[PDB]
Length: 129
Ligand SMILES: [Cl-]
Ligand SMILES: [Cl-]
Ligand code: NA
Ligand code: NA
Image 1: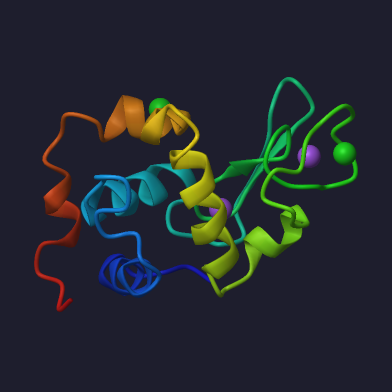
Image 2: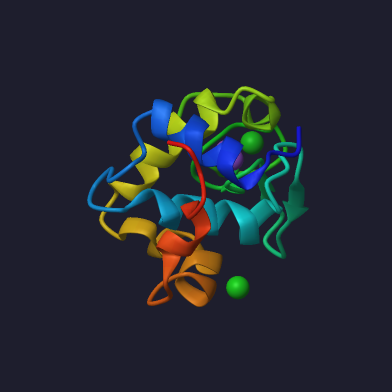
């Protein structure tokens, strides 16, 4: 599913991401925009053979099992394909583990490069939340 901006904000808010570990909702929307263009079905392969899955492009080297990333961990205990669902629950819960792992949202390179230090509240402006 390709989310609307406000629709995703709303879904993320319902799932407890608004200010999760200090990151306001606009951060999460911004990151999803640049990681996946709000498409839950987004995948991208990395040079290392790992793959990024879903709206927040969670990586199979550490966070999920795709059966093809040798030597990898599955720290969210989920098949990576669960991250592609139109229900963002699995993406959102795994993201909460990632953002808690010491590096905050710097774990998402697109956030660091495209969102961090910008006016991220613009991503939720106009939305009925
Ligand atoms: Cl694997
Ligand atoms: Cl980037
Ligand atoms: Na994801
Ligand atoms: Na894995």
